[PDB]
Amino acid sequence: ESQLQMVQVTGSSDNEYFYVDFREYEYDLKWEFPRENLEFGKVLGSGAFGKVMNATAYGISKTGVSIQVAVKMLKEKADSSEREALMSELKMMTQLGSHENIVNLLGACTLSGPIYLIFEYCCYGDLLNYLRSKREKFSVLTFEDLLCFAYQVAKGMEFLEFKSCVHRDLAARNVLVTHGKVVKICDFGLARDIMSDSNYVVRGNARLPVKWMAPESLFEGIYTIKSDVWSYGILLWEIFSLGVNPYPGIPVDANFYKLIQNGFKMDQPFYATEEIYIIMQSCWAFDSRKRPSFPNLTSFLGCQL
Ligand SMILES: */C(=C\C(=O)N(C)[C@@H](C)C(=O)NCCCC#Cc1cnc(Nc2ccc(C#N)cc2)nc1NCCC)CN(C)C
């Protein structure tokens, strides 16, 4: 199941909404891409039931010009139920529209065999590992780069809000990096190693990114765009600490739930100004109504002078 979800609001309060399921809608065949034109490199990431692989795609955006892509597909085992979820995700992406700060869909392969979802290739990998690799080479990474990253992510989330979407797993690990230090919001859970990664906690059918979740998500299972603001705040702490695990040194257990519930907030990270930290704290307002909006955040980050 995709952590990126389209929703429809049915009331003024947080819990009044439902998730849009594209299972019954029809797939627009204009996205179909010839399978024989995918020369696969090798794996970029692997989940329990699916993986994203390197691939060279010829003709997908300019004839005579072959480019590199990332192809989300199902694992060698592939019973019918798993494929419909990949189809539903595909359909949703076809209807989202493209944006610079989103890992965009480029095409798909669904007819003559196994399902391939073709996305942009991001040659610098995920933002988390990117920042951690620049811990030595920092002043090469600068403060403005951090501010630009923050801005681009907020822009991407603004686009998702405009498209009535929510991202139930927003974190620096789900942000990718390309040319021009451009970052794109992504979502892989079907192709994410979800539990050798200790940031996800298994609870029934759910795999919860606990340290990134708003209280209403943690305690009531409510996911709104304001939940994303909370998660964005956490992601901000990741950026301006150069990739430190949130609530460093604090284990995910029953005590953690009590901490968040009682209003625990992280301290100012080293590479952040007092202004940026004030913004973080507003994202971590317990009452979802008091958190800033992504249009607010996106505008304010004209701080890059
Ligand atoms: C480009 C720099 C460059 O080419 N490198 C630094 C090379 C040496 C390199 O090894 N890059 C890092 C490879 C690790 C990676 C990756 C990666 C890239 N793109 C995706 N895209 C993607 C798209 C959609 C989904 C979904 N759903 C998932 C992923 N994914 C990954 N890794 C997957 C886990 C993050 C600059 N240049 C051209 C000089």
Image (cartoon, grey):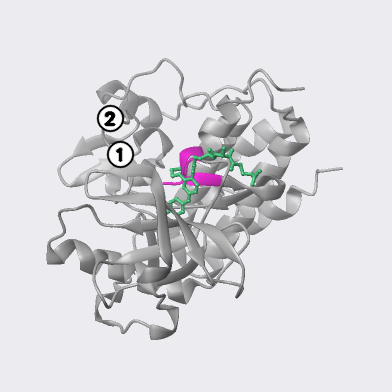
Structural distance between the alpha carbons of marks 2 and 1: 6 Å
Pointers 2 and 1 in contact (C-beta within 8 Å): yes
Mark number displayed over residue 87? none
The percent coordinates of residue 115 (x first, y second) are 28, 67
Amino acid type at mark 1: Asp
> Given the current orientation, which residue lies at the most extreme top position?
249
Residue at horizontal 22 percent and vertical 49 percent from the top:
49
205 left or right of 304 in image: left
Q: Position of residue 231 (x, y in %)?
A: 48, 43
- Is residue 249 depicted above or below 91 in this figure? above
Q: Secondary structure at mark 1?
A: loop
SS state under label 2: loop
Toward the right, the furthest residue is 305
Residue drawn at (77%, 37%) of the image: 144
Magenta stretch?
Answer: 168-176
Say whether residue 29 is visible.
yes
Picture coordinates of residue 270, whole percent (x, y) = 66, 20
Quadrant (top left, top right, bottom left, bottom right) of the N terminus: bottom left
Q: Residues within 10 Å of mark 2 (few under 14, many from 20)?
A: few
The residue tagged 2 is: 196
> According to the image, label 1 marks what residue?
193
